[PDB]
Every structure is written in structure tokens, then in C-alpha cells.
Amino acid sequence: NATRFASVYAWNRKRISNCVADYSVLYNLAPFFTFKCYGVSPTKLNDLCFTNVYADSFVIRGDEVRQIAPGQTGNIADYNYKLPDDFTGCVIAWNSNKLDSKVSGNYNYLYRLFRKSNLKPFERDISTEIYQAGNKPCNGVAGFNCYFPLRSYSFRPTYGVGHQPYRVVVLSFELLHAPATVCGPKKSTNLVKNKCVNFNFNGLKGTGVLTESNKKFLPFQQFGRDIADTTDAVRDPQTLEI
Amino acid sequence: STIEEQAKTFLDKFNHEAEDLFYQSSLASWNYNTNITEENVQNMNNAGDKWSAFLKEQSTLAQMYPLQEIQNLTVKLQLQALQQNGSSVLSEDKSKRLNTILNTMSTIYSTGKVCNPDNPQECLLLEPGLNEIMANSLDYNERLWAWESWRSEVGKQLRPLYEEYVVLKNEMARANHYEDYGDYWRGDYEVNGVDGYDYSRGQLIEDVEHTFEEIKPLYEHLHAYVRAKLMNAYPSYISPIGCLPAHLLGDMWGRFWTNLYSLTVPFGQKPNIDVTDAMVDQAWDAQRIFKEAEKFFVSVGLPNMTQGFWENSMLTDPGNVQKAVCHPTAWDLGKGDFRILMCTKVTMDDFLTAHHEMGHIQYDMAYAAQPFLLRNGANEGFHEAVGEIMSLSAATPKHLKSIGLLSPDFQEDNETEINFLLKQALTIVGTLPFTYMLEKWRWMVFKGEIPKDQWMKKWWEMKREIVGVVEPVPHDETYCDPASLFHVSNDYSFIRYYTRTLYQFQFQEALCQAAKHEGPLHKCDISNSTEAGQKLFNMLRLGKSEPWTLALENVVGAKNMNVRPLLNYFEPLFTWLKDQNKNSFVGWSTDWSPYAD
């Protein structure tokens, strides 16, 4: 929900690490235009989580959302950015006709359509290289069969479905050998007392009766044990009470 | 560094402001057609001159080393639409004079003022005025004024203005390694790089001649049917042996024969098929007429449209304070978007153009992720040939029953479809030899084999042996009959209307062979068939990445331009015009003249 963004070859690295993800206001409300992705479903992201999450901010056409796919070739998918075969993220697009556009042409952020070679996945290429396709060199200028790359946007909110400003935020997920740090939301239930019920806590699982405790405790603890090494205490994960 | 690895990187800093400098002249021309103010015309000029200089700034810096090192087929087919230098190969006094002669040629065509020389005290406006007085005036002296005087006050100074315009037009194309400007319209038809499917520019001269030989039995029976029905209207003006006069064809020149339908009715006891009387009872508005017409696009198998089409484009004229020009043009404004500006009324001709102008949207929708040089037609006439397949399928009485339009018990005999097919004969077949004799006139005055005195004498000698009309007065070498139209004065291509009627018929003859329709092809409707879109989806997405020779292989399978879909579409029209022409004269002759008294 930013007010600015970046180019598709000048991708910033929003390093989401050591966070708590809240998808009850973003995924469940869904104020975006389309909500469709592959690999991992968005309903599995609340019950499964990953090591490092990386994000970006780039606005493209509505015709280039078919190019954002794992294993895709074509116009954008080999020359501006590339999605790998192990892509476990999701791609969300939203029409930004009232925010990201500009009257009298949008002449500020640039994008490409071709390249010298096939780039690597998540490659930040900001080069202004001089091309030579034939047998005579170009000395820095374009020519017959000599071309040059670097041109900006054409956004305006008065037209149809093809090249409206669509803000695409690719939330790339990555599971490594390191333990997880950013995990999504999970629902809670009510708490009943003075009854033989089961326990499903943040770090406890068992069956017992919840009564009022009269002992002292440390707030950085999860549970406590008695003199016979049995679990006789539980801290609430929401409130500071045992 | 390797020669084989380097394919194509032109589309970075060319193909992103080829739209964007045209974008700033796109809405500025669109606001010129909706909000005609004093400052909404100035933004067309300074932004359109930046895009006009963009095609000449990169052309001067593309003059280094030649073409023959390329290997890929995708490189060469987009290279032909950029290496045309245009006007930038002439001098400073010759190239900029072409820009000034094109602005004075479109001004007097739109703002012309010509009226009666007998009583010039009341002098009227041309374009809403003279377009509608041709239909209702049943007089010989009244129709003589609207054809002769219009080329006598507007077209009198174009004859010393078109002679040096042709001479400068030869210099800009002979330096572009072509033989003439005559193959500049045939430069889009040039196919090279594929073995077995090579279509040169010299092959197109015999191909229009090959498809014109078999239309001469079909056109001369329509030439003898309008003439035989004008005996009770004009008893002593039109000869039964000779040709028809050219000042009574219904329009300003005689391209369309649409106003000659009400006078040549075959049977007056049965009513015509009409949506206009049944529209005002159910109270339709502007939201209905595009939504059920877009239901025709879903049922073949093309996907839906989002909210950007309904809140941006309007269908109602924005008040009576501000003037809005509403000519039917589907706005192809760059890399796959369409805003529709149409002054819609309760009119059957407005209803068929709702399917026509949305048929140019569905061609550019499929290659919306393709480059802009491939975002075009397969030729110039390929864009409007795939647009009117939705209008001829919506004029079918089997389609009107499934929606809820006309009466559910309507009689359909053999004498019902003949009045519909002769309405299509003056829309499709009636403009077909008229497209031939003007494009052959364009291909005979550009090469320069003829002198200046045979410039206009060759024009009226072709019309008495190709289309079968004769002028009532003779013209000298100071007037111009073909140069008073919309396409020739604003420098547009006229080859695109001969291939409009040919590529449309090739697609509709095979579309319900997939949908399994038994009967004639004027009862063919392409709706309620999900497998009918899959034959089109490999054709709607090929644009100019594949040429027009390989584009016809997946529907009809003919690599050449043939006339055989045009014959069995009109199979009651070939049989029922034969028995009524037993005693009249078949064809025309070159001896009758109205001024040879």
C-alpha cells in the first residue's frame, strides 16, 4: 500500500525477516483486482511458513501478468525478470488507476522488453550497454541492425483492460535450512475453566482441569513443572496470567 | 560477440515510446472528438509532432550497415515496419512541403462550401446536407447538381495540386529500394523468409486480376437488375442496352449502393426484417446494447471484459452544449486497448456497427502481450475483415430468436432471404468492382507511363468497362472525379477495402463447418459453440509474427486469394436473378453516352 514504487529492472529487496505476518487484513479482505497464484495456494500460507520472505514494488501492464509464471518464456519472463522452477511465492495484482498513474504521460520509471542474453532468476540488471548485432561496430549509437535499450512508461487511467497501471507485488517465499522467522496468522478460541478438557496451546498439549494458580512465575516462560516432573502450569499466550 | 547469438534487442527503446508519444496524441485526438474546445486541439499538435519527429529521429541514426546477417524469422517480419524512412530522404525544401500540402488537402474536403449557381442566395453545408438529399430526390435535374458541382468548385484546384504531389511521392519510395510508390501499399503484402510461401509484390498484380474474372457473371446480373427496375422511375434517361448514369447511384461517388435499396424492392407485399419498431416497446438503453453483444463474444469461447470498458467509454452524447463527432472508428490506440465513442441511436444500422466496431477489439485483444509492430493486421484490410464477421452473423434470423428480439413465430420461405441477400449484395458485391478500378487507377498514374493529357481521360474510360457507369457531362483536364473522397484526400490506403470482402468470406465459410451447420451460409451463426473459438484463437493471436500466407492455413487452408467463398454464399442470388433476366441485356456496352445527343 505504498505511494511510490520502482522499476522492474531496479527491484528493491524488501527483506521480510523476523516478523509476524498478518493475512487476515490482506488475504481475507482482498481489495486487489485479481487474486490468483500457482505453486502454493494462499489458504496454505496460514498453516505453512518459510525462512526468508522477499518483496518488491513494480507496476506493469495487464498483458504482462501472464508472463509472470514459473517456467515461462516470452516477452518479459526472460529479459526483465525470471521466476524459477522452485518458486513457492504468490503473485498479486491490483489496478491503481487513482494512485500510481500520472496525467500527460508517466515518464519516470523504465522497463525493458529484450536483452543480450537470458538472465538469471532475481537478477538486478541496471546496465545501459551498447548492442551490436552485425559485423561492424556501433561506437555507442544505434543503427541499421544496431539497437539500444531503456525507455519509460505510458500510464493513464482513461483506457481499457490492456495496459492500465496494475501494481504487482510478488511476495516471494523461500524455505531454507535455517529455522522459520516469519509466519502467518492462526485463529484462537475461547478459554473454559474448571472442566476436564484438552489442551492445544502454543507450546503445550495435554488434558487437564484449569484452576486458578496461586504461585509466582517469570513472564518469559511457557510452562512449569512440579516436584514429580509433571506439567502443572500453563501461561496464556495472549494475557499475562498463569 | 558471436554472430549467431544476437537476434533482436530493438524493442526496448523503440517499442515503449512508439505507443507513448502516440499516447499523448491518442487522447488529445479523442478529446478532439468529444470536447471540441479551443485548447483541446492544441494538445494534438505539439504532442503529435513529437511522435512525427520520433519516426524521423531514429531513421537518421539507422544508416550504418545492411540487413543480410539475420537468421531468425521473428526478426525480419517486424523489421519492415520500421526501416521505411518516409519523407526524410528528400531536401529541406521538398520534404517539408509534403507536410503543408497534406494539411490543405483535408481542410477543403471537410469545410467545403458548394451550392446552386442558379440561385446562390441560400447556400448549405456539405456533409450533413448532401449525404441525405440523394435518397429522397426523385428528379433528374436535382441529382445532376449534387454530383457535378461538387467536383467543380472543390475539385477544380486539386487538379493543379495533385500533379506535383505524385512527382514528389515517387522520390520517397525509389530511394527506399523499391520500384515505385505503387508497391508501398503492397509492401505489407510482401512475404519473405519462408520457403514455399513466398508472396512478392509483383504477384499481387495478377492476383486481383485472377479474382476479378469470376465476379463478372455475378456483377453483370446485378448491373442488369437495378437498370431494369429504373424504367418506371426514369423512363427517358437510362438506356436498356447501355450503362447506368453515375449521378444516381445513391451517394457522392458510387462506392456504396446503400440508398438504392428502397427503390429496387423485388416484392413489396412482405415486410423487411426490422428491429427498429420492436426496440421502443421494451425500452432499451445504452447499457443493454453492448452487454448482449458481448454475450456473442463469450459463447464462441473468447474471455470476458473487466470494469475498464464500462466506466471509461460512454455511449450517450454528452449534452447539447458540447459537440462530439461520432464517426464509427474502433480506436486502436496502442498495445491492446479500445475506448469506444459511438453516438448510438435506435437504428438497425447502429446495431450492426456495434458488432462491427467490437470485432476490431477482439482481434487486437489476443496479441495484446505481443510487440507493437506485431500489433497490427496481417495486412491493412485484415483488421476490418475480421470485424464484420460479427455483423453478418447478427443479421441472421436464427440468432435473433435465441435472445428474445423478434416474433417467435416468423415465416421463413425462399422468397424471404432473397430481399436480405440483395441488401448484402449492395454492401459487399456492390463495392467490389468499385474498389478495383480506383486501385488500378492508382497503379497506372504512379509509374508515369501516361502523359498529363491522359490523366483524367483514362478515368472515365475505365468506368464504362469495369463498373458499367457513364458520366452525364464530360470533363476537361482541370477537374478531378476520383480525388474528392475521404481516403484519397487524407492519404489513406484504398487496397484495404478489396481485401475486406475477401478475407471475411474465407473465415465464415469454414467457421460453421466446425459448428456443423446444414444449409446456406446466410443462415450460419457461430454462437452456442465452444469449439468454434479454438479455430480462431490460433488465428487471432498470430498478428504480424506470422504472415498472412500462414494465417489462412488454420481456418480455410488456402495460401492464395480465391473467389470460391464469394460464389456459394450467394447461391439463391445466382439462380433467382437468372429467370428474371430472360429478355433484358446482359452486361454493358461502350456506345451509350448521355451527352451524345
Image (spheres, coloured by chain):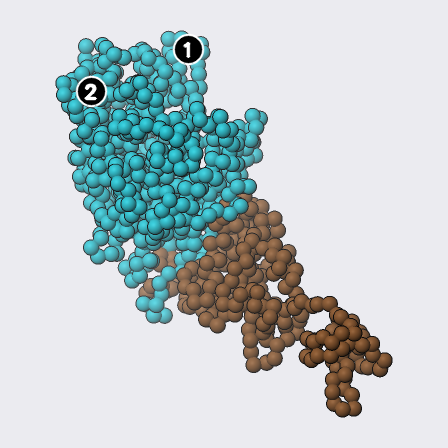
Residue B346: x, y in percent?
46, 27
Relative depth, front residue between A240 and A184: A240
Quadrant hosting residue B144: top left
SS type, badge 1: loop
* Vertical placement of residue B392 versus A88, above or below: above
Residues at marks 2 and 1 on the same chain: yes
Compared to residue B228, the image places residue B106 above or below, namely below
Residue corresponding to mark 2: B243
The amino acid type, in three-letter code, at marker 2 is Cys
Chain bearing mark 2: B
Residue A181 visible to an observer of this rendering: yes
Image quadrant in which the C terminus of chain A is located = bottom right
Quarter location, residue A10:
bottom right
Q: Chain B appears what colour?
A: cyan
The reply to whether residue B349 is visible in this rendering is: no
Horizontally, residue A78 falls left or right of residue B587, namely right
* Chain letter, brown in picture: A
Q: Name the residue under label 1.
A: B120
**Which residue occupies 57% across, 61% down?**
A169
Residue B308, how many percent across, how many down?
52, 45
Residue type at the position of mark 1: Pro
Decide: marks 2, 1 in contact (CB < 8 A)?
no
Residue B112 bears which disc, if any? none
Q: Which of B61 and B17 is in front in this view?
A: B17
User: Which residue occupies the foreground of this view, B466 or B230?
Assistant: B230
**Foreground label between 2 and 1:** 2
Image location (x, y in percent) of residue A68: 48, 62
Image position, residue B167 (x, y; %): 29, 35
